[PDB]
Amino acid sequence: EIVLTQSPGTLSLSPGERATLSCRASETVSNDKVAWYQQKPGQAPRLLIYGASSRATGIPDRFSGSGSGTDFTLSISGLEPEDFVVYYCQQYASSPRTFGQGTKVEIKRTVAAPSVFIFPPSDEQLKSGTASVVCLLNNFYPREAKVQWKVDNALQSGNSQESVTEQDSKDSTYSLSSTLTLSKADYEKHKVYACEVTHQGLSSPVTKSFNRGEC
Amino acid sequence: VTLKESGPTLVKPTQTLTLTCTFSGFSLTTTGEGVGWIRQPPGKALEFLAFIYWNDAKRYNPSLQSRLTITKDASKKQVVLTLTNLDPVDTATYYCARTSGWDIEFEYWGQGTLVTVSSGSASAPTLFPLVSCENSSPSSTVAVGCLAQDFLPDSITFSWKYKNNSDISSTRGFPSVLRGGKYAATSQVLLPSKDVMQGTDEHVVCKVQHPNGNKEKDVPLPVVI
Ligand SMILES: *[C@@H]1O[C@H](CO)[C@@H](O[C@@H]2O[C@H](CO)[C@@H](O)[C@H](O)[C@H]2NC(C)=O)[C@H](O)[C@H]1NC(C)=O
Image (cartoon, rainbow over all chains, first blue to last red; front, side, top):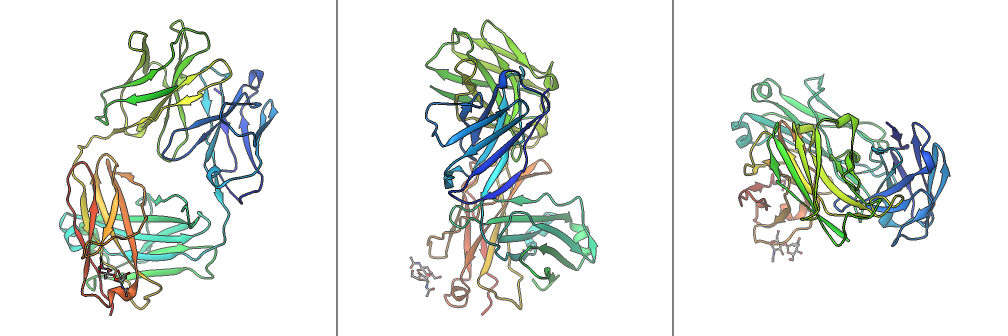
C-alpha cells in the first residue's frame, strides 16, 4: 500500500510561466516506476510521461520529468491555456497500483466582487412539502469562499451540500450555488432567511434577506 | 488502438453490476500487455479496482479483495467485469485502458460510461419557478433562474428563450449534487433591467431536454419599473 499525496491542491499560474507539480510517496518505489497522467473534465485521461523520464508518442517535448526515490517534480515550459487541467501521478511498481489525489491549476486573475442573489421558494413548490432557498454567487475570485446560512439569528449546519461550477473559458471566474433544504412545517416557523457571503475583495460582509409574504 | 465501454446506466443497490470493455486491433498474447479498470467518483480522484496480466494472471486490491472478479474471453476479445454489493457511495465512471509493455502503462484510454447506483427510479424532472425578491438595490442587472429537481440520470441541457421564442446566451450551468438519493441542479440567466421595464413580455420559458419527459415551465419576471 503506497500512499500518494499531492500538494498544493490548487495553484494559480499565468500563461507562459513555469509550473512545478509535486508528488509525494509514502515509501521508495523500485526502479523509479512512476508515471504522470493528464485528465480533462468531460473527456478521458491521457498518458503523458511513462517511467518519469520517457515521453510517449504524440506528447510535446515541453513536458519534462525529474527526481527519483520518494521525490518527483514535473516541470512544464511554455504554459498554455489548454493545459489548465488536473494532473495525477501514479506508480506501477506496486501491483496492485495506487493513484494520487491530483492537483488542479487555475488561471491567475484579479479579484472581482461577487454578486449575491436569493430566490424565495415558489408557492407551487411549498405545496409539495419541500422548501428550497438558494444563494447564488457569481463572478468571484479566488475560488475559495465561505457561504454561511443564518435564519432567525441561528447559524445552520449539516444541511448545506454546496455546488460549484468550473472556471469560465472566456471570463476565468467562478460561480457556486448554495441550496437550503428544510421541512415545510419548519419553514412556516421562520420569518427571515439570509445567507452570508464573505469575500477577500469586500471590506465588510454583505447580507441579503427577504420578508415572508412579500414575495 | 481504441476502447469502448458498455453497460447498464441504472442499477439498484445490493445487486450485480456487469460491464464490458470492447477493444479491437490487438490480442492479449504478448507479455506485458494487460487490462485494468479505473473509476473516478465526481469531485474525487482516480481509484484503482483491479488489473489482469497475460497467462490468466490477475491482481486485486486488498481494500476491495474478495469483492471483485476478473474474467477474460479471447473469443470475443473483451474483458468482463462483475461488481457485487453495490453502494451509492461507489457510484463513478469506469474506464479501461491497454498497457503496451512494462513501462508504458495505460497508453490508450476509451470513453467510459456513467453507472449510477440509486435506490430511486428514473423519474421525470420537476421544474420550479424562481421569483427575484431583490429590492432597494437594482444593481447592474436582474437575474432569474430555473430549479430542475428530481432527475435521474444526470443529463440535462439548459436553453433560455423569450416570449417571442428568441435566443439567449446564458452558459450558466451548475453541476448536480446527490441529495437524498436524487440529483438536484440549478440554472440561472442574466437579463438587462431595461428590457424588464419596457416590452410587455412579463415572463420567459425554461426548457430542459431530458430523456424522461419534455415538460417546460415558465418563470415570471418580478418586474421593477
Ligand atoms: C423578442 O422581444 C425582445 C424584447 O424583450 C426583443 O429584444 C429587443 O430587440 C432588439 C433587437 O432584436 C434586441 O437586440 C434587444 O435585446 C431588445 N431591444 C432593446 C432596446 O433592448 C427581441 O428582438 C425580440 N425577438 C425578435 C426575433 O424580434
